[PDB]
């Protein structure tokens, strides 16, 4: 259908892409304690639950 | 600069070295320098022939 005149300028990024493959280098650690039960997610060497 | 460009996803297999240095980096600058630091006289050698 005939509508109002349309002037549109679009800006896009050149989304250069390297495919995300399955992660390698993750370690599953399991331990028994009475504190901070469940997963703890120590991604960083420095931070540790006290 | 080459390492950074590869880390972004460009394919510089065809681009010449000069064109590689041409490439836009986006607010990052990489430079290298060569200098030699002088030192004061510390040890003196002297051999005298009679």
Image (spheres, helix red, strand yellow):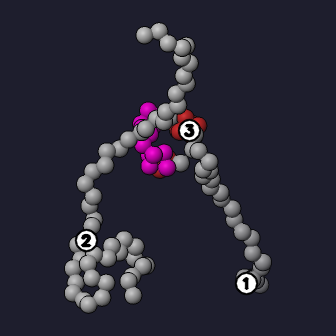
Q: Name the residue located 54 percent from the left edge and 14 percent from the top edge.
A: A4
Mark 3: secondary structure = loop
Cα separation, mark 1 vs mark 3, equals 50 Å
Please tell me whether residue A12 is drawn above or below residue A23 in the rendered image: above
Q: Is residue B6 magenta?
A: yes
Please tell me whether residue B21 is drawn above or below residue A38 in the rendered image: above
Q: Name the residue located 77 percent from the left edge and 79 percent from the top edge.
A: B41
Query: Is residue B47 visible from the viewing direction of this image?
Result: no
Please tell me whether residue B38 is drawn above or below residue A22 in the rendered image: below
Camera-nearest label, 3 or 2? 2
Q: Quadrant of the C terminus of chain A?
A: bottom left
Residue A27 circle label: 2
Cα separation, mark 3 vs mark 2, equals 39 Å
Residue B34 circle label: none
Q: Name the residue located 39 percent from the left edge and 82 percent from the top edge.
A: A48
| Position of residue B29 measured from the top left corner of the image (x, y, whole percent) | 62, 50
Res A33 quadrant in image: bottom left
Q: Earlier in the sequence, mark 1 or mark 3?
A: 3
Query: Does label 1 lie on the same chain as label 2?
Result: no
Q: Are marks 1 and 3 in contact (CB under 8 Å)?
A: no
Packing grade of label 2 (10 A; few <14, some 14-19, many >=20) is few
Packing grade of label 1 (10 A; few <14, some 14-19, many >=20) is few
Q: In the displayed orientation, state which residue is furthest to the top.
A: A2
Q: Which residues are magenta?
A: B4-15
Mark 2: secondary structure = loop
Cα separation, mark 2 vs mark 1, equals 57 Å
Give the residue pinned by disc 3: B23
Q: Name the residue located 35 percent from the left edge and 75 percent from the top edge.
A: A42
Camera-nearest label, 1 or 3? 3
Residue B43 circle label: 1
């Amino acid at each position: 259908a005939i509508g109002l005149p349309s002037i549109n300028i679009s800006f896009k990024e050149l989304a250069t892409t390297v495919k995300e493959r399955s992660a390698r280098g993750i370690i599953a650690m399991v331990l028994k304690d009475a504190k901070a039960l469940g997963l703890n997610e120590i991604h960083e060497k420095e931070d540790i639950p006290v | 600069q080459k390492s950074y460009l590869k880390s972004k996803g460009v394919d510089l297999s065809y681009m010449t070295l000069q064109e590689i240095k041409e490439a836009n980096t986006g607010s990052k600058v990489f430079l290298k320098a060569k200098i030699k630091v002088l030192d004061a006289m510390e040890d003196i050698d002297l051999s005298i022939e009679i």
